[PDB]
Amino acid sequence: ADKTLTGLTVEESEELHKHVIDGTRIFGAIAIVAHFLAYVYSPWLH
Amino acid sequence: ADKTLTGLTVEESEELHKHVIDGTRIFGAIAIVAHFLAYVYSPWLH
Amino acid sequence: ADKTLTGLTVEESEELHKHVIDGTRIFGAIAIVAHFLAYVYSPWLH
Amino acid sequence: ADKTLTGLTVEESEELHKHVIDGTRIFGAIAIVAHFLAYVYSPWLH
Amino acid sequence: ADKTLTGLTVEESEELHKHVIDGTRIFGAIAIVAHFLAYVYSPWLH
Amino acid sequence: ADKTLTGLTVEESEELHKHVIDGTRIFGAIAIVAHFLAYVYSPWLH
Amino acid sequence: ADKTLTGLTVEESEELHKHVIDGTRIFGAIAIVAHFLAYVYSPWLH
Amino acid sequence: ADKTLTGLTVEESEELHKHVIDGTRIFGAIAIVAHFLAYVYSPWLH
Amino acid sequence: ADKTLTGLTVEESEELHKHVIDGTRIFGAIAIVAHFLAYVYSPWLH
Amino acid sequence: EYKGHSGHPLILKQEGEYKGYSGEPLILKQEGEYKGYSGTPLILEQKGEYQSFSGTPLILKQEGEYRGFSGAPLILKQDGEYKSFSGYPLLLNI
Amino acid sequence: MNQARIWTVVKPTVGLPLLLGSVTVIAILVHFAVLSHTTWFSKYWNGKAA
Amino acid sequence: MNQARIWTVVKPTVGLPLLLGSVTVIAILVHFAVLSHTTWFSKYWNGKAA
Amino acid sequence: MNQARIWTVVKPTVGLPLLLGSVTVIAILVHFAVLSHTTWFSKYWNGKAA
Amino acid sequence: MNQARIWTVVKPTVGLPLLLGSVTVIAILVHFAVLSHTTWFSKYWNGKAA
Amino acid sequence: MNQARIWTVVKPTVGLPLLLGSVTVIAILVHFAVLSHTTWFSKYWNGKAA
Amino acid sequence: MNQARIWTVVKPTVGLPLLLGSVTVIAILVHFAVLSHTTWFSKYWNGKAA
Amino acid sequence: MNQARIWTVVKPTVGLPLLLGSVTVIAILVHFAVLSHTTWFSKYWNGKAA
Amino acid sequence: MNQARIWTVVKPTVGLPLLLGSVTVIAILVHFAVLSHTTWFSKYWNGKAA
Amino acid sequence: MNQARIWTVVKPTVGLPLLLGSVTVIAILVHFAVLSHTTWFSKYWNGKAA
Ligand code: BCL
Ligand code: BCL
Ligand code: BCL
Ligand code: BCL
Ligand code: BCL
Ligand SMILES: CC(C)=CCC/C(C)=C/C=C/C(C)=C/C=C/C(C)=C/C=C/C=C(C)/C=C/C=C(C)/C=C/C=C(\C)CCCC(C)(C)O
Ligand SMILES: CC(C)=CCC/C(C)=C/C=C/C(C)=C/C=C/C(C)=C/C=C/C=C(C)/C=C/C=C(C)/C=C/C=C(\C)CCCC(C)(C)O
Ligand SMILES: CC(C)=CCC/C(C)=C/C=C/C(C)=C/C=C/C(C)=C/C=C/C=C(C)/C=C/C=C(C)/C=C/C=C(\C)CCCC(C)(C)O
Ligand SMILES: CC(C)=CCC/C(C)=C/C=C/C(C)=C/C=C/C(C)=C/C=C/C=C(C)/C=C/C=C(C)/C=C/C=C(\C)CCCC(C)(C)O
Ligand SMILES: CC(C)=CCC/C(C)=C/C=C/C(C)=C/C=C/C(C)=C/C=C/C=C(C)/C=C/C=C(C)/C=C/C=C(\C)CCCC(C)(C)O
Ligand SMILES: CC(C)=CCC/C(C)=C/C=C/C(C)=C/C=C/C(C)=C/C=C/C=C(C)/C=C/C=C(C)/C=C/C=C(\C)CCCC(C)(C)O
Ligand SMILES: CC(C)=CCC/C(C)=C/C=C/C(C)=C/C=C/C(C)=C/C=C/C=C(C)/C=C/C=C(C)/C=C/C=C(\C)CCCC(C)(C)O
């Protein structure tokens, strides 16, 4: 290997990004539920 | 084992996160009580 | 080649910019669809 | 024991935190007196 | 040659400025067209 | 003894604090007089 | 000669300032024209 | 004697503070005159 | 003579301050003129 | 290679002089001393004591030993220990 | 899912705090927007308006 | 609970102050929001309003 | 597509966060602008005005 | 009381000034909030209003 | 076109972000200025005002 | 008086300016608060109101 | 024209960006000032007010 | 006159500029305060109000 | 004229930018103050109001 600017290897950067992708998916799924609840109970889109 | 960017070992990072998780649970528990008190005394959700 | 101010080689800088260009094109593609939907549903340009 | 990220040993960190805990207790105690005085002289909770 | 304050040689600084001048000229051309459209459609200069 | 995080010895840190305590007491004394004059001349507490 | 706080020699400093003086004079000239145009077309000084 | 945290000796610091003290006395005397003038001409304290 | 905190010797600092003093005196002279012009043309002090 | 999703090329591939899009020249070289487009001269030399325009003196010299225009004393003596003005005890550490 | 090597060039101790902070600031701003520009969100908090 | 290794890439002296500070700022913002967009919260502090 | 070498002189850990951050800030500002100077955008959120 | 080791990972010259400063800022914000959203606090300072 | 040597004394990682950022900030400020000081710009966004 | 050792962990060049500065900011804020929420303070500065 | 040695004590990468930025800020401020405190500047942009 | 040793622990290039700057900021604030909460200060600048 | 040695303890690349910047900021503030608290300054820019 050779030094990246940050010092994370390509593999360590990919393992870090798995958490970032999974975090975005979890945030999205919760936000989808929050939008469904906001639709169900607010006058939005009614 | 290998050196990390922050200097903490994986074992030290997991120990630190236990305090973060415990603190988040304590904060959540107190927040739940505060919402219950607010619901009882304020006109919200009535 | 020679060392640069940021430490990235010319090849590394070019491979990085490919993500920036592709990201800009993806952002533009989504933004175009957003403008089309905005037009189809909002009173803008009507 | 080994060098910490901040340089303080476990004993020094614990001795430092004692002042933080005592300080929070002193602040809390004075705040309770201030709330009592406020309750007595202000129309709050009346 | 001698070490510059930024580390870029005079030759490298000139090639960088070529992109800055080109960028300014491109930005100016797009801006000119945008101003022409504003004149044609907005009540400005009417 | 060992080098503190700030480089000040215990004796130096305590001798510094003596100015902070004295300075706080002097500030308090002036502030008390300022409040007395405010009471005597303003409509506060009347 | 001797080292300077900025690492820029006296000759390089005087040559740098030439661009600053010329830039100020060019800014002043354009500004003078802008004020003349503003006077001719706006109600200012009328 | 030992190297201070700032590098100034006790003597150099005391000579520096003389300018701070004198500067404060100069500022204070000027401000006193400004208050006398503001009193004589403004409706304050009248 | 010894290395100062900033690196400027006593002679270099005194020479720099001459430009600061002359710069202030020039700013003052220009400001005095601007005040006279403002007085002659504005209703201030009239 | 970065495959992308938005078609190809993603970057331009030529080498040498930057063939900028907005005609040429892109810059003006200098063979030597900068000449102002606002003409000349640009600089006034310093060759000794700084020439004021605002008369002289420009500074008041101090002999490594200041004495103020508010006279004296400017500081209090301080030896053996700090002297408090607000009485004692002054610390109560453990 | 193709950007994974960004952490070879953006410091994680910078990009992750800025990512989580920015997402949170956006969420706060969207709440304050809907709160300022609807009647019903304020009304939901006011409830019976005791 | 699975993000425990974040402290190997994000400095604790940075993430922990930012986390505790952000939670505090969010709490303050929610209080000010409800305080401005409701009547009962202001009424609670005003009490008898004598 | 010809500026690809900009990353040899501008640090990626600086330019990329500033780029992604600015693009996000611009989008936020454009939303607030349209929200503050139009009626239909607020009307869309208010819906039935329940 | 179980967080005593936080000072081994958070610099005291950072966490302590931020802690003391945050507490003071919160106190100031609470005073300004009550002062703005209540009548009696302002009336207390006015007193006789002479 | 004669200032090309500026990058020998001003760091590209500083001057380039400040240049591109300032130009963008100015464009935003101009749009907000025209939007808040004219009637036709807001009317253009409202369109039919439905 | 028992906190005398805080300067062993908090840098004097940081804590001393931040202390004196914060104290001054509080004093400024208290003067502005009383000035904004009272009549007699403004009345004192107007005096004869000439 | 006699201050040419300022760059020997003030770093060019500091003073030059601050100079150009400050001049641009001053210009922006003067435009906003005249735009707010005059009628004709707004009228010029509004034109026929179509 | 007894604090003279503060410069042995507080960096002059930090505290001394911050002192002069703070004193100036305070003076500016006091002018703006009296200008906003009085009539005679504004009246003095208007003079004859020509 | 007796403070000439200030530059031995205050860095010129800090004190000189702060001095020139502060004096400029002060001038901007004084212009905005007189502009906001007078009629004739606005009238001068408005002229005939044509
Ligand atoms: C969803 C569709 C994909 C897409 C898929 C393709 C395909 C497929 C091809 C290219 C190819 C090209 N792409 Mg691409 N590309 C997109 C976005 C862009 C954008 C942009 C939005 O700014 C740009 C400037 C480019 C640039 C380019 C050129 C380098 C090249 C030749 C132009 C062409 O005919 O394209 C295709 C042109 C059009 C489809 C006409 C409209 C073009 C405009 C400028 C953008 C339309 C975006 C659209 C609204 C996104 C949503 C579409 C819906 C999914 C239906 N792409 C999006 C992300 N691109 C070519 C290539 O490199 O082949 C090897 C090619 O054949
Ligand atoms: C889009 C066209 C290109 C362009 C293409 C050319 C061409 C072609 C030539 C030059 C050449 C020159 N260019 Mg160029 N150049 C542009 C932008 C600029 C700008 C600027 C906008 O401020 C400047 C100052 C310059 C500077 C110069 C001089 C060094 C030189 C002589 C002037 C000239 O011929 O102008 C030409 C420009 C005009 C007379 C007016 C341009 C009007 C508009 C803005 C552009 C043309 C219409 C276009 C279809 C509109 C769409 C723009 C897109 C939205 C980007 N370029 C843009 C980005 N440039 C010459 C050269 O080097 O020859 C060897 C030359 O013949
Ligand atoms: C031409 C205007 C020049 C100027 C040119 C001179 C000259 C010439 C001399 C001095 C000398 C002196 N100057 Mg000088 N000086 C100016 C500004 C100043 C200011 C200030 C504005 O606060 C101060 C405090 C000083 C300080 C001093 C003393 C160190 C010294 C002795 C006083 C004396 O004899 O005064 C005499 C009277 C004055 C200096 C005039 C004071 C009135 C001010 C300047 C009026 C406003 C501006 C005026 C209308 C001119 C137009 C300015 C342009 C628009 C920029 N100068 C400006 C920058 N100065 C003298 C010296 O060294 O003696 C040994 C001397 O011979
Ligand atoms: C003259 C005003 C001086 C002062 C001069 C002295 C003197 C003289 C003595 C002390 C001593 C003491 N001072 Mg002291 N001190 C002042 C301000 C303070 C303040 C404060 C919040 O203002 C505090 C908490 C203290 C603390 C203390 C105690 C450690 C101690 C008394 C113990 C005791 O029996 O306690 C119970 C009694 C008290 C806590 C009362 C302490 C004094 C009060 C608070 C002073 C009020 C000042 C008044 C408002 C304004 C003065 C005018 C100008 C503003 C300067 N000082 C001011 C700056 N102090 C005494 C000691 O024990 O020394 C061995 C002693 O002899
Ligand atoms: C009409 C006049 C106005 C008014 C106008 C002003 C103005 C204007 C100002 C003040 C200022 C102050 N006012 Mg007042 N003030 C009013 C009425 C009040 C009321 C009230 C409930 O009515 C209170 C509580 C106060 C109290 C105070 C202080 C908070 C503050 C001076 C600080 C000081 O002395 O620091 C020095 C510190 C001390 C004296 C404490 C040390 C000595 C003590 C005795 C020792 C024990 C310390 C203790 C154990 C430590 C606690 C540890 C905790 C863990 C933190 N005023 C009235 C309504 N007041 C000033 C200010 O803001 O200063 C910052 C200010 O400028
Ligand atoms: C708001 C209201 C109502 C009222 C406010 C009123 C008010 C107070 C207004 C105040 C206004 C003021 C103060 C305006 C001041 C304006 C000024 C001063 C403008 C200056 C412009 C300077 C320029 C353009 C400099 C360009 C420099 C350049 C290009 C430098 C290039 C350097 C190079 C190439 C390096 C060479 C390296 C090597 C030597 C090795 O070759
Ligand atoms: C306010 C009003 C009314 C009006 C204001 C109007 C106004 C002015 C509007 C202006 C709008 C503007 C200007 C909009 C501009 C938008 C732009 C430019 C969008 C750009 C998007 C870019 C993206 C998405 C980049 C992604 C990069 C990525 C993901 C990079 C990934 C990098 C990696 C993986 C490292 C690889 C390392 C290796 C492996 C090579 O070593
Ligand atoms: C205002 C108005 C009206 C309108 C405005 C409208 C508008 C513009 C809205 C815009 C909204 C936007 C843009 C929203 C975007 C949202 C996004 C993108 C959310 C992303 C969430 C990401 C998460 C949750 C990441 C968690 C990462 C995690 C936990 C990472 C963990 C890492 C670890 C453990 C280290 C590993 C160490 C090792 C293994 C290597 O050793
Ligand atoms: C306020 C109101 C109402 C009204 C008044 C408002 C007001 C006053 C407005 C004033 C507006 C002004 C002043 C506008 C000025 C605009 C300007 C100047 C725009 C300039 C654009 C420049 C660009 C786009 C540069 C791109 C550079 C780039 C991409 C550089 C890339 C470099 C590379 C790849 C080389 C590195 C690799 C190696 C060579 C080493 O190999
Ligand atoms: C708020 C309301 C309504 C009202 C109240 C507002 C209020 C309170 C206002 C207060 C205002 C105040 C306080 C104003 C103060 C103004 C002053 C002090 C101005 C000073 C100007 C100084 C200048 C121009 C200096 C130029 C220096 C220069 C050019 C230096 C050059 C140096 C060089 C060449 C290096 C040489 C290196 C080597 C020696 C080695 O050769
Ligand atoms: C806004 C509304 C409506 C309501 C808000 C209400 C509200 C919340 C108010 C809160 C107010 C608060 C909290 C006020 C607190 C005030 C305090 C704590 C004041 C402290 C003053 C301290 C001083 C003066 C220290 C001087 C130190 C000094 C001079 C140190 C000198 C050091 C030296 C010489 C170095 C020696 C080195 C060597 C020994 C080696 O030689
Ligand atoms: C908002 C409302 C309504 C109300 C608000 C009310 C309110 C809170 C008001 C508060 C006001 C306050 C707090 C005011 C405080 C004012 C003070 C403290 C002024 C101090 C002035 C200090 C000066 C002038 C220092 C000059 C230093 C100098 C010249 C130093 C020179 C140094 C040298 C030569 C170094 C080389 C030397 C070597 C020996 C080494 O060679």
Image: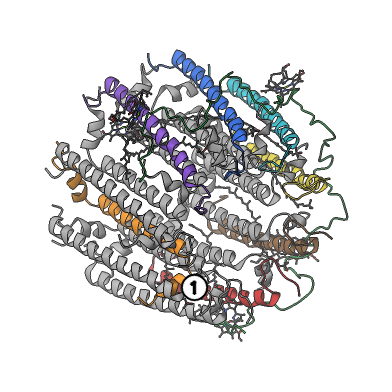
Chain colours: C red, E brown, F purple, G yellow, H blue, I cyan, J green, L orange
**Visible residue check, residue G46:** no
- Quadrant position of residue I23: top right
Nearest the camera: J83 or L6? J83
**Visible residue check, residue H7:** yes
Question: Which residue is the site of mark 1?
Answer: C32
Find out if the beta carbon at label 1 lies less than 8 Å from the nearest ligand 1 atom: yes
Label 1: chain letter:
C
Nearest the camera: H38 or H12? H12
Q: Dot 1 lies on which element? A: helix
Which quarter of the rendering shows the N terminus of chain J? bottom right
- Quadrant position of residue J64: top right
Amino acid under disc 1: Ile
Q: Is residue I21 toward the left or the right of residue H27 in the image?
A: right
Residue J72 position in % (x across, y down): 57, 19
Q: Is residue H16 above or below residue F3?
A: above
Q: Is residue J91 toward the left or the right of residue G40 in the image?
A: left
Q: Is residue H44 above or below residue F10?
A: above
Residue F15 position in % (x across, y down): 46, 39
Q: Is residue J53 above or below residue J41?
A: above
Nearest the camera: E44 or E46? E44
Seen at 80% across and 63% down, the residue is E11
**Crowding at label 1, few (<14), some or many (≥20) Cα neighbours within 10 Å?**
few
Q: Is residue C43 toward the left or the right of residue I43 in the image?
A: left
Nearest the camera: H28 or E42? H28
Please tell me in which quarter of the rendered image ligand 6 is found.
top right
Residue G8 position in % (x across, y down): 77, 49
Residue J65 position in % (x across, y down): 66, 26
Seen at 43% across and 30% down, the residue is J84
Name of the residue lying farthest toward the right: J31
Q: How many marks?
A: 1
